[PDB]
Image 1 (cartoon, rainbow, N blue to C red):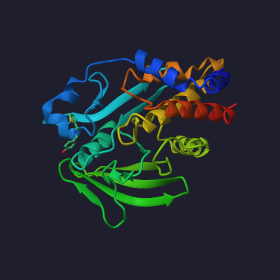
Image 2 (cartoon, helix red, strand yellow; image 1 turned 180 degrees about the vertical axis):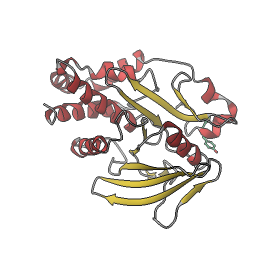
Image 3 (cartoon, rainbow, N blue to C red; image 1 turned 60 degrees about the horizontal axis):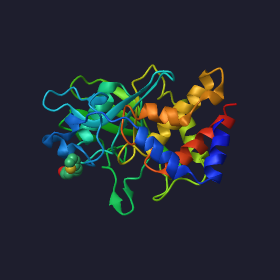
Image 4 (cartoon, protein in one colour; image 1 turned 30 degrees about the vertical axis):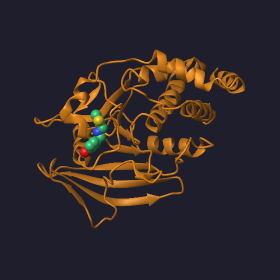
Length: 281
Ligand SMILES: Oc1ccc(CNCc2cccs2)cc1
């Protein structure tokens, strides 16, 4: 049982040690498309790249590249697209990806500005009457409604394909209270947020995979997917304590590098799953 594993690692202060063994054991696959000189300006960070085998391709003939990965969790029957916070020049590619993959939800785990720098382009409209048009990808995005709560904001958006005049409703889930440094003290509001995403139908197999991002698409984004998958496997299995969070993280790391950026994010992921298991058992 992970709860006893938690106390052992905590009492021995072994988090940095566990974390390094995960780093050591993590998969390494080629990222040749990401490294092509012409894709430099499509990448936020030079050391955060999608693997070629799991990368999302845009259906545009010129350049199919976006910094996004498909994470397929076969036993849990859950998929996720993890991506970076869009750049000023990739906002149109972002929405094209949402469209092409039939996603119903976008999960954002960062503020546009943190530590006095921009972590992400403002890629959705701030007012109903001021819609956004992405001329490069022929999409229009309208804010329909915005529900602001203490720890998160939910937005209903309308995405229109200007080429075919089809429209879809997209839900934007914006977790607004992740602190600038470290991790939340309590996983309560994060779990509350994760259950709200689940309740929306955004994680359901009827729809395309949910799009999840922070700034790099590996740290906070990693914590979200890791907690969701671990809780789902505990519902599914004959023995819920067969779930090993380290094995699940390593399976997820076959699809995108660097998921869970610090030993504190790892400790927080354990705390979230342990606390979430109480509300599921
Ligand atoms: O216009 C832009 C200029 C640079 C960047 C960041 N690129 C980071 C790097 C990726 C690969 C090698 S260096 C984004 C937009």
